[PDB]
View 1 (cartoon, rainbow, N blue to C red):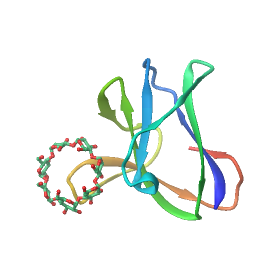
View 2: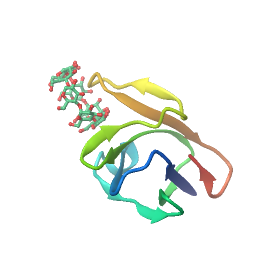
View 3: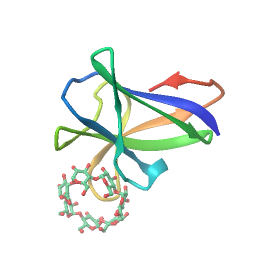
View 4: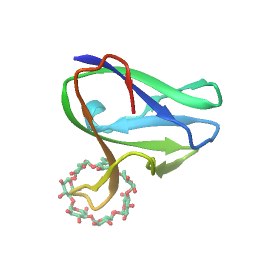
Length: 87
Ligand SMILES: OC[C@H]1O[C@@H]2O[C@H]3[C@H](O)[C@@H](O)[C@@H](O[C@H]4[C@H](O)[C@@H](O)[C@@H](O[C@H]5[C@H](O)[C@@H](O)[C@@H](O[C@H]6[C@H](O)[C@@H](O)[C@@H](O[C@H]7[C@H](O)[C@@H](O)[C@@H](O[C@H]8[C@H](O)[C@@H](O)[C@@H](O[C@H]1[C@H](O)[C@H]2O)O[C@@H]8CO)O[C@@H]7CO)O[C@@H]6CO)O[C@@H]5CO)O[C@@H]4CO)O[C@@H]3CO
């Protein structure tokens, strides 16, 4: 697994990260420079995720998106060879 950084820049007071990599639980993100950050060690390959921002599910319009099998919109990124790449 590679260290991988998620950064929410869309504002809010309290933000959780939810994704395929945590079985769609809600990881509290750390407030940092007016943004929210979380760092996970993730295997190389595809990951879907979304944000829970002040009680509302939201995706990041600046990362790629895909429609899940549930009929919902997730972000989709690919972890590659770069420690601490930011998504
Ligand atoms: O919890 C896991 C989950 O979290 C994230 O989903 C959140 C999402 O981002 C929010 O927007 C909100 O979702 C609500 C949504 O906006 C509403 O539209 C409504 O959803 C309705 C759908 O619109 C509608 O399509 C229908 O859904 C049916 C499906 O069409 C049908 O295919 C089937 O779904 C089953 C799947 O086929 C199956 O794969 C399995 O789903 C899993 C996903 O594949 C997987 O990605 C993950 O889902 C994430 C998700 O991607 C995030 O965005 O986990 C799933 C397993 O838990 O299971 C499905 C059966 O449950 O069945 C459904 C009908 O049940 O109906 C709904 C009406 O409810 O409501 C949404 C809120 O419930 O919230 C979610 C978190 O809840």
